[PDB]
Amino acid sequence: MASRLLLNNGAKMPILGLGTWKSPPGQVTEAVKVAIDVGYRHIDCAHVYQNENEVGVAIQEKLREQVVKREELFIVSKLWCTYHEKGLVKGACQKTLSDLKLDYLDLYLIHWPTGFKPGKEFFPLDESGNVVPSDTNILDTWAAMEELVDEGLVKAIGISNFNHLQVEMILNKPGLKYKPAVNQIECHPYLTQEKLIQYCQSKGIVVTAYSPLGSPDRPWAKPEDPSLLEDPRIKAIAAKHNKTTAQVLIRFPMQRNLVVIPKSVTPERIAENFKVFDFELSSQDMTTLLSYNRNWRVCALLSCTSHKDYPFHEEF
Ligand SMILES: NC(=O)c1ccc[n+]([C@@H]2O[C@H](COP(=O)([O-])OP(=O)(O)OC[C@H]3O[C@@H](n4cnc5c(N)ncnc54)[C@H](OP(=O)(O)O)[C@@H]3O)[C@@H](O)[C@H]2O)c1
């Protein structure tokens, strides 16, 4: 199990990264510092997580301390939905770069295929509780993303939460300059993404699996919800390998040739989560974990189910 995957832009991406959604600003600096110390070289960020400045502080201080150099880090951020307009993309990227205190990003993703009404609300909703869209489409936004590469602000561009038809649309875009390097999607044993993964990988697009632990700190969590980390079938596989359930859920996508980005602000867990290069899940382990699929999403973007570009009506 090698530590990095080759992207279609020629760059190598670490298969294990640190997630930062829900990581409070006052805690994420320490989280990122510990992460770097124990070997993470990939941090997944987003303007919408509203902690990019404090992530930036951690990176800047580890660079200053000569712990790591910039070339050795792989920093990922994402274009928020209110910025899909071609004229707004560069600005939003520069804001993220400014917050992160970086010259460039290694990877910049379109966060969701759905464009929102531009303005100061992250989620402009109307009286029906539905999002107020922007008159934007994925192809023009992609052209704008491409320009960021040409200008050297980002080394790679990609997408997130795109279904295979949406990916195909970009791949077939008239005048396409750069194929998406990565499609970051929710993936774990309750949402295995077999067809979407097979499609992306057949196209040379690397898949990053998010919420691999099932996002137990998700705002909407209810006691009746399924729980990956407490699934006795999964705990059993974990016990057999003498690893924690989390380490199993992290190793699972790695063996599918996926990048995985578990989130923690807990120093002990950050270290524990990285300790997954010292064991293997058996072939049957993988088959069994795959059999647990139930099409269950943590992130269903429910306020946007009428958006023309809502990604989760399609089968995959
Ligand atoms: N592109 C997208 O639309 C999208 C959507 C969702 C997420 N993401 C990205 O993917 C990242 C990870 O997904 P996520 O944050 O939804 O959830 P996750 O990584 O599946 O789960 C994180 C939660 O699990 C806990 N945890 C972490 N390590 C643990 C361990 N070893 N044992 C027990 N509990 C543990 C964390 O607690 P503590 O933090 O308290 O330790 C936190 O509550 C996000 O941070 C974000 O970077 C992207």
Image: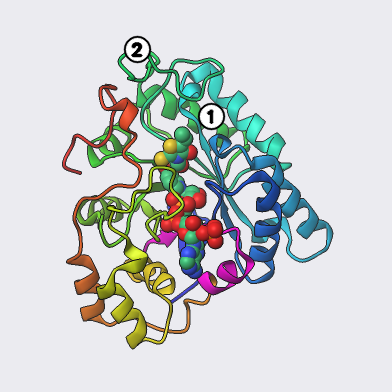
Foreground pick, 28 / 148: 28
Question: Which disc number belongs to residue 127?
Answer: 2
In this view, 286 is above or below 186: below
Position of residue 58 measured from the top left corner of the image (x, y, whole percent) = 73, 53
SS for callout 1: helix
Q: Which residue corresponds to the image point at 43% horizontal and 60% vertical from the top-left? A: 259
Residue occupying image coordinates x 42% and y 81%: 243
Where in the figure is residue 171, as x and y percent of width and height? 31, 37
Residue 122, above or below 183:
above
Q: Name the side, left or right, on which 314 lies relative to 231.
A: left
- For label 1, the residue is 147
Left or right, 282 with reference to 40: left
User: What is the magenta range?
Assistant: 257-273
| Disc 1 C-beta below 8 A from ligand 1 | no
N-term-proximal mark, 2 vs 1: 2
Residue 267 image position (x, y, % from top left): 63, 67
